[PDB]
Amino acid sequence: LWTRAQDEVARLKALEELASGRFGFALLGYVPVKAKPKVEEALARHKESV
Amino acid sequence: SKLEAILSQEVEAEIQALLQEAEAKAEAVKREAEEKAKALLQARERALEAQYRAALRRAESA
Amino acid sequence: GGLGLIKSLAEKEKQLLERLEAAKKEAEERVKRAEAEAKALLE
Amino acid sequence: ELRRWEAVSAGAEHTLSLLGLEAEPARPFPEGLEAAEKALSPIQAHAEGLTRQKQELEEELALAQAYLEPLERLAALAHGLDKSPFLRVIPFLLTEKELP
């Protein structure tokens, strides 16, 4: 329960760093070049392949 | 882009749905008032028909 | 990129909200015509 | 909802602290917030009542042991006028043999 609550609280606190576009949203950050395939595989599970 | 297309699609579909919901509810409101007007003319002319009946019967008796 | 998403989201909310209020003004015209026909039929 | 989940996490941390266990990470428990709160609150309430009863009983045992034999000796000495309405008995756990 502490693990699931820490994950949900992390998602909630990370939602505060977002940017809203009046029923629109985006996220920006940094990621290493060696994780571009892992980031693409994570983005493969997107709703419309965002 | 594609994201502009899908967000414009969803917002346009929901303002379309708002149009449909609001105008259907407003027409369902107005129809009862119009039928009230027609049936009120019916009952009004029925009461005035009773008045015409009273006038003919009293002219008969006189 | 980031600033491209900034510009795109600004244009997104601008054009979608402007279409929204244009459609609600045409809804206002529909309401006006409907009560005009209502009062013409009642009179 | 974020405040509710944060309060659930803080209550789980306080329950683990009162349980004596440490914050060890593991696999999460995927469920709703209400059922997880209902599961957490039962164990937290049982542990809180047990810890409060244990702390109160330990304090009571320590306070009883601090003046156990002397209260018995003073009551055995004052077993004739304990609550008689003519004489108050000031008892004092005082120092060594300087009774004058």
Image (cartoon, coloured by chain):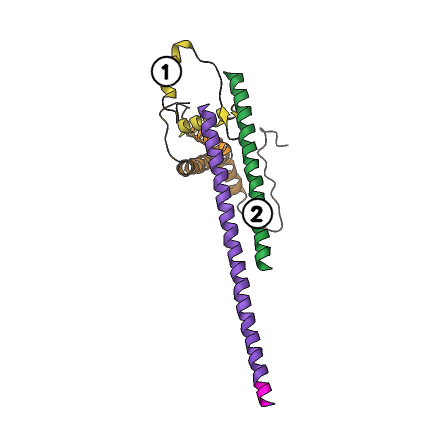
Chain colours: A yellow, B purple, C green, D orange
Tag in front: 1 or 2: 2
Report which quarter residue D98 is drawn in: top right
Which residue is pictured at 55% across the width and 25% down the height? C11
Position of the C terminus of chain B, as image quadrant, is bottom right
Q: What subunit carries mark 2?
A: C
Crowd around label 1: few <14 · some 14–19 · many ≥20 (10 Å) = few
Look at label 1 and name its amino acid: Lys
What predominant SS class does the magenta segment belong to?
A: helix
Which residue is pictured at 48% across the width and 26% down the height? B4
Question: Where is mark 2, residue-wise?
Answer: C31
Nearest the viewer among D22 and C25 is: C25
State whether residue D10 appears in this view: no
Look at label 2 and name its amino acid: Val
Q: Residue furthest bottom?
A: B62
Residue D31's disc is none
The residue stretch that appears in magenta = B57-61
Question: Where is mark 1, residue-wise?
Answer: A38
State whether residue C22 appears in this view: yes
Q: CA distance from mark 1 to mark 2?
A: 55 Å
In the rendered structure, does residue B25 fall within the stretch colored magenta? no
Nearest the viewer among A44 and B57 is: B57
Crowd around label 2: few <14 · some 14–19 · many ≥20 (10 Å) = some
Give percent across and percent down for residue D92: 59, 36
